[PDB]
Length: 167
Image (tube, rainbow, N blue to C red; front, top):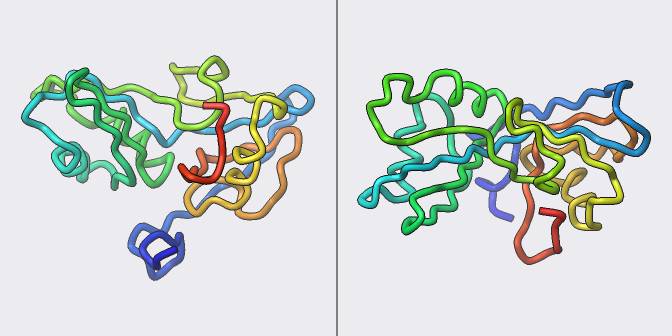
């Protein structure tokens, strides 16, 4: 891929990819923190670039999927910290009609706690591509560490060509 698409220290979108292990998770389950925000009430005149720019003080945006007719978007930012920063501080005045909350970017929707923005996922409910992306993604994921019971990581990037998803 191109150098801008690589999570490396000379890239200005470089982010560390924290991985931890949680002994409370059930057997053959993993924990994944979302980096994806669901934004509803997107004005009709507002496009992908507008959403990216209005969020820039709080978080650098990686991708936007905007359904303009339905007036909502899914916005993936480069790190979990940045996503939490958005929910904590963005549009607290209600100056814009945008309502922001946790989205799911990875794994089945029914595994997600939408209040806290993470999923406890049984490994059998991941596809082969989900598992591959979890370990080999540029942003999020485990950075080569294999998936085992208890592992905790940030939402990994997924690649549209290369597999079906549990999402």
